[PDB]
Image (cartoon, rainbow, N blue to C red):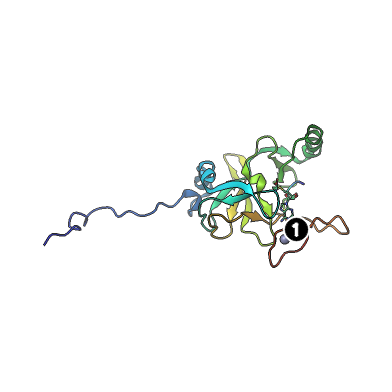
Amino acid sequence: EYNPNDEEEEEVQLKSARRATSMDLPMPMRFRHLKKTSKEAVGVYRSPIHGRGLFCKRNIDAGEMVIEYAGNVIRSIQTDKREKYYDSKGIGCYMFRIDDSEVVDATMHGNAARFINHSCEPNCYSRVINIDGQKHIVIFAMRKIYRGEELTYDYKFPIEDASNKLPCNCGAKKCRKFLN
Amino acid sequence: RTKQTARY
Ligand SMILES: Nc1ncnc2c1ncn2[C@@H]1O[C@H](CSCC[C@H](N)C(=O)O)[C@@H](O)[C@H]1O
Ligand SMILES: [Zn+2]
């Protein structure tokens, strides 16, 4: 009797390759291909939460690197002046604070990370990582995220009080009603 | 509004 498997007995078995951004590797190895991978993983579309949002185009694994919050690192004491300059030119300001003395300015050289909306029940979180003496802000998935789902994280604004309150439209059952 | 650091 003939057997289709007789020639396969010694062959390498194949399966789906796991993306480096998703694997249990040191950060620099995961980060190396984040830019290319992110362009495949996510896109900017109209959102039911607010204006435009970032959405999943292709399943994202739990704990995988989604996208870097790209921009130029500046000192914390430059922000105010920069905000006034942009405001005076009709330019939308986008920044993400790294620590007390450093901030990422995504206004002029940012990417799609700028469009991530807030949610009181998020599916993403963020981390600061150092690669080659350079600080980067990286967004990770808290859970498996599926094609079509909106990516959100918790802005966790310091609780203002009055008035001063900005309403939240995240639509989560556990919504806090205000962004602050 | 500059996204905060306590975010991390
Ligand atoms: N859960 C939420 N509820 C109400 N407004 C939100 C929100 N998440 C983000 N926003 C709005 O988006 C701003 C941050 S920038 C996020 C992208 C924005 N949707 C845009 O189209 O450019 C916030 O200051 C707020 O104005
Ligand atoms: Zn909410």
Residue A170 shows up from this direction: yes
Which residue in the structure is indicated by mark 1?
A168
Q: Quadrant of the N terminus of chain A?
A: bottom left
Asked if ligand 2 lies within 8 A of label 1, the reply is: yes
- Residue A122 drawn at (x, y percent): 65, 59
Q: Amino acid at mark 1?
A: Cys
Task: Name the residue rendered at 58%, 56% in the picture.
Answer: A149
Give the left or right position of residue A120, taking residue A89 as reference. left
Residues packed near mark 1 inside 10 Å, few (<14), some (14 to 19) or many (20 plus)? some
Residue A128 shows up from this direction: no
Q: Quadrant of ligand 2?
A: bottom right
User: Image height check: is A102 above or below A8?
Assistant: above
- Residue A46 drawn at (x, y percent): 65, 49
SS at mark 1 in the image: loop
**Depth order, front residue of A95/A2:** A2
Give the left or right position of residue A130, taking residue A170 as reference. left
Residue A85 sits in quarter: top right
User: Image height check: is A147 above or below A95?
Assistant: below
Give the left or right position of residue A169, taking residue A132 as reference. right
- Residue A84 drawn at (x, y percent): 82, 36
Give the mark count. Answer: 1
Subunit under mark 1: A
- Residue B7 drawn at (x, y percent): 70, 54
Q: Quadrant of the C terminus of chain A?
A: bottom right
